Amino acid sequence: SKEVMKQMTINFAKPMEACKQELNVPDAVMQDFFNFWKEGYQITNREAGCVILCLAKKLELLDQDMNLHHGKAMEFAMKHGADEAMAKQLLDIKHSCEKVITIVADDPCQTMLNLAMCFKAEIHKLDWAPTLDVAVGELLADT
Image (cartoon, rainbow, N blue to C red; front, top):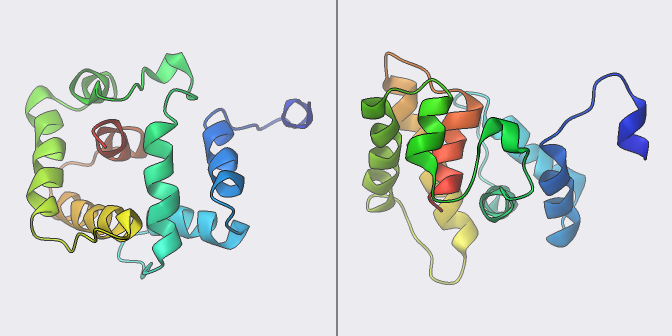
């Protein structure tokens, strides 16, 4: 009822507000994920990964109009303006990063955050930009 009322309302917020309470974490650390997308910005917090990995399961929650579903990244990414070469590149960057980053057996949040900040590192270098729908979407879809 409340998210009806205002002129601007956010479709992708339903898994995101759900993650914050589901994980039993403060509003401070879900906003660490919002700050994370700012380039070079020094997000080191273990909770940032914990929220990030949480969306990847909860893509089911997302609106069908953006076409995001888990495992469907190659098809999804192309709908968001990636070419087929560039789509496989985001998946290639991820798996290339996974082997160089610290992976923690105990803590999947460090594995996700360390990967994500490595993944963003590579698309920063590139002459083309994926959008937040597609750059995160291929990561989150292929979690």
